Image (cartoon, rainbow, N blue to C red; front, side, top):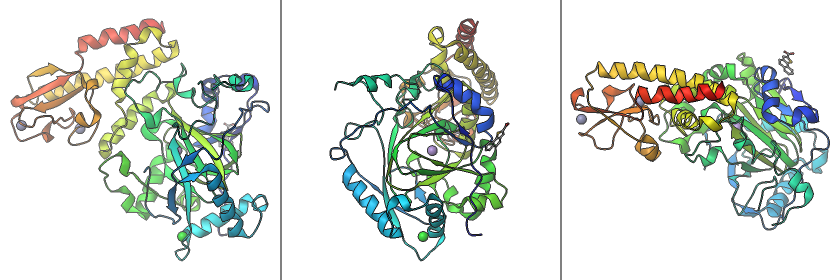
Length: 453
Ligand SMILES: O=C(O)c1cc2ccc3ccccc3c2s1
Ligand SMILES: [Cl-]
Ligand SMILES: [Mn+2]
Ligand SMILES: [Zn+2]
Ligand SMILES: [Zn+2]
């Protein structure tokens, strides 16, 4: 009547043999899990990474959160772990007039959706979210301090979320252009009702979340194929979230009842993630949720070979929306081509196919701007420019393969889709700036082909 819980998402329990290689495992479950957007992974019973920390020496600055459905929040923006924990336990204890382990999960869920929909309730909560640093580090073992033999067992686990971004079957690895918010783990300190709004990952990447300890985290997920249905439902009910934003640090997001989505025929799934379990989200899969109580989680983005074509589609979609990029997809592709001899052979093969499309599109774009009367040209090392100095004036895309400039407007650039948007001068005053000639590009793709055999 009031809240009807969505159906449960898939839960996998891999054997030690299946578990050994995360990328092989993720590829295996993909046909099931991409139908639901999120899934849960329970490691083998004896896989237990040790967790240890001083609750008095870890400090962090908390964010404050109002809990109202459809109200705008911004995506990104002092306690010790002990003092936060004391605040969190007392809050839950007093809210329900109960001891915390006796508060049923079904009840916290029901109550969460009651309180966010009710205008006359003004519940505020706090939480932590930050990338690993010296003041607050990874929950997984890392190399530095002498480690116990148990900790060194987990140092090079593929499921140690520090290693995940730099494994061989991973794609975001050899990226030199720093993208700190996308290759490093984030740490999250939760309390009862603190929540994460509906969103998808930057560049439509995968994400993987590990709950180290504490009370469960409740998740809702939507499969990738339904991303645009969800957005249309959201646009109708809260248009303010969809106005154009001046940068990446101004993304607007919101809390919204999954029953609202289910009423509009958007498929939604749920899960309670407990301590010691993994949740994985797939490309373009919308997700949100809330914490049941005091807890500690760690998460990281990643990109497999399966993702490469979607990554190209994502940047195209960013262009239509005038959304800023975190990195240049074409720059990453060419960086990998330049390292073709050390690439894994399946990677080399998949990169080669994306490069072939890149080259065909670039050929056609250069033919088009030549016919507009752009004649002069000069080579340019785009990867050396800071990102804010190579975004298209019109669509904000990060340039790499090519761009148009004019001496009339020093420093400004447009991508080749927006030649008409640079300035009022005739096109013979423009220059085509390019990273590679077509003749440079075909040998790069050939090296990939040889490596792939
Ligand atoms: O091809 C198959 O055998 C399966 C398809 C689905 C679809 C949604 C699902 C949602 C929750 C749990 C399992 C599924 C499965 S299993
Ligand atoms: Cl409220
Ligand atoms: Mn996420
Ligand atoms: Zn553009
Ligand atoms: Zn001009």
